[PDB]
């Protein structure tokens, strides 16, 4: 469920769920994790771009088919582990990582995007974190967003549950760039070439230092979040 | 010193100190805490709005003369503890909380407001944190504001001691909305109805998770602000 | 390598490296630390302004040819310890501190500036954190910047390695004011007089509380950054 192509030293991973909105099914997680592993392990690769695809959403979050079909505690507990593992998978890529966002980045897709070093979105795209509106728990989201963007910003976002257009994302500093849908991928690749040109020894050790507290946060959130979602999933 | 009213599932707590600027006296603390307890314990309540009242300040905070008048240290311990307990009282409300700010939100009033889930202010209102200007210590304000809005933002506010009108609060992201004084209360209630419509269990457990570090911070600050006036 | 003047209760420390870009050589660090010590220890001083000088940079930081030289594990460590000690030196000044920025504030100069209570820059000045562009490690810069201004802001800055002019710094909230180069020093001194007029008890204890987490973070970053500038 992911294409892997190359713009020279740049590896481009394109999400390809049967569904245009690239929902994170368990199969898609797997592919995305595996592609990231290969990219990180491959010396020909010096930078990575993850992309929803032309006329496709970055990801509309997890698979509503998994989520709505969750009752057992065993089942929910392990689902949270999966989710974090995915986010960690991105954070542990020792090379530069760009997220090219078009369409919708919702809930899990929003969060997934926040794991990247940089984010460019289309002028026509949207971010959303509408969990509580819908009756889903959002401790993991709160945790991430609080860490990346501050307490009061996070509060606003998760409690308002609004559809964030580009102007709004810029205002929140959720993205580094806004371009036309047609221009988006090339723009992302360029950013990747730029960061790829920074000496590797320097960039890897710095990125590691930078992402350590983030990883550590996510690990701490693991247990407590299993608690809210176990309790929430009974309606 | 409050009015408790209802817009259906929304409880509206209106501060009513004899003084139009709703200063936090001991008595007002008490009422506000008790009204919050009831609202949180009441089934019929699904969201809470706290409001200074029409043609009234949200709250000018606590008397700096009386703060400066405390010279026994348990006087200060008692007082520090009271202040935090108030802020914790808000943070422990398991339902949505909106603060409708008109007039002045000063010192304690500024801080008290930061405990809420959301904040709307009037176009004509002002936030201020002037403690250092008036020769008051300011650990608790800094601690809170650093946590809610970042180090460098807090630095600027505390050290500059300026009256922050609405444009400035928006720029700082201190509020979620600015409206006319006449429109403010209805606006706040609407927000409350919106958040009240969120499936409770999912909301409550999330809010608990969210506010936990905040509460823990207030506890750390309690100990520290009293290690100060002890040495 | 520093000239110490007085505007009444305000002490003004002007960086004076032979090089007009005030690079942080070991000698300059020393002078700056010693001038800060004296200013903090001097009762006649109630506030401090640090300035690059007219027609001179605040500081272009350390020399990236020398940094890339350091291969011996001691050399790396002692250098890191020095760098932090400098930043701590500013944080431990118990009186108000203003940084008057003209020219370039690069890497160490950017970071050094973030230690101050307030920052004014010239309209014509620039901030830069270009370490990764030039193959220099940046754990320290990121640690600081993440703490002062948030994770995602720090990310953007260190990964983009751009020259931030004034409009951009305002947009990032890196400074409290932008003025003409000619006006800059007087502006800084005024800010210093303003903060100097706040009661010393009130200020000193608050500032201590405020800067504690910052110091504690610098101390962690020290122990850590060794292992990465090592590898
Ligand atoms: C839950 N809702 C959501 O995740 C989002 O709000 C969206 C993206 C589904 C809303 O987008 P819309 O403008 O409503 O387009 P629409 O709902 O008609 O298309 C979505 C399609 O992808 C599927 N889909 C969208 N998001 C998800 C998701 N997160 N998980 C699983 N499937 C999804 C929808 O079921 C629908 O599939 P279909 O062709 O089998 O019916």
Image (cartoon, coloured by chain):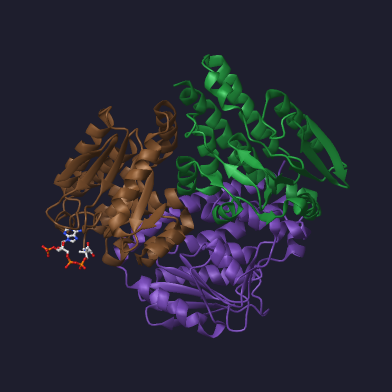
Chain colours: A brown, B purple, C green
The percent position of residue A163, horizontal first and vertical second, equals: 33, 66
Q: Is residue B112 at all visible to an observer of this figure?
A: yes
Q: Is residue B227 at all visible to an observer of this figure?
A: no
Locate the N terminus of chain B by quadrant. bottom right
Figure check: B149 above or below B20: above
Q: Nearer the viewer, residue A9 or A212?
A: A9
Locate the C terminus of chain B by quadrant. top right
In percent of the image, x 56 and y 41: which residue is there? C128
The percent position of residue A103, horizontal first and vertical second, equals: 26, 60
Picture quadrant where residue A167 is located: bottom left
Residue farthest along the bottom direction in this orientation: B182
Taking the image as shown, residue B117 lies to the left or right of residue A54, namely: right
Figure check: B14 above or below A143: below
Taking the image as shown, residue B138 lies to the left or right of residue B87, namely: right
Picture quadrant where residue A2 is located: top left
Q: How many marks?
A: 0
Figure check: C107 above or below B32: above
In percent of the image, x 41 and y 68: which residue is there? B96
Q: Quadrant of ligand 1?
A: bottom left
Q: Nearer the viewer, residue A58 or A208?
A: A58
Taking the image as shown, residue B193 lies to the left or right of residue C187, namely: left
The percent position of residue C195, horizontal first and vertical second, equals: 76, 53
The percent position of residue C16, horizontal first and vertical second, equals: 77, 33
Q: Nearer the viewer, residue B57 or C142?
A: C142
């Amino acid at each position: 469920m992911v294409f892997e192509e190359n713009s020279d030293e740049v590896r481009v991973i394109t999400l390809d769920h049967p569904n245009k909105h690239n929902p994170f099914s368990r199969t898609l997680e797997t592919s995305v994790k595996d592609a990231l592993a290969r990219a990180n392990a491959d010396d020909s690769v010096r930078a990575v771009v993850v992309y929803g695809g032309a006329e496709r959403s970055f990801s509309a979050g997890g698979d509503f088919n998994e989520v709505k079909q969750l009752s057992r505690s065993e089942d929910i507990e392990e689902w949270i582990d999966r989710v974090i593992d995915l986010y960690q998978a991105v954070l542990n890529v020792n090379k530069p990582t760009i997220a090219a966002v078009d369409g919708y980045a919702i809930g899990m897709g929003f969060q997934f995007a926040l794991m990247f070093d940089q984010r460019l979105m289309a002028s026509t795209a949207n971010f959303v974190m509408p969990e509580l509106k819908h009756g889903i728990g959002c401790s993991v989201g709160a945790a991430i967003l609080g860490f990346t963007h501050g307490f009061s910003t996070m509060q606003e976002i998760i409690y308002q549950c609004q559809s964030l257009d580009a102007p709004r994302c810029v205002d929140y500093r959720l993205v580094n760039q806004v371009v036309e849908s047609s221009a988006l991928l090339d723009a992302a690749i360029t950013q990747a070439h730029v960061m790829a040109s920074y000496p590797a020894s320097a960039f890897i050790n710095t990125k590691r230092a930078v992402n350590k507290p983030f990883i550590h946060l996510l690990e701490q959130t693991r247990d407590a979040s299993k608690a809210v979602h176990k309790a929430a999933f009974q309606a």
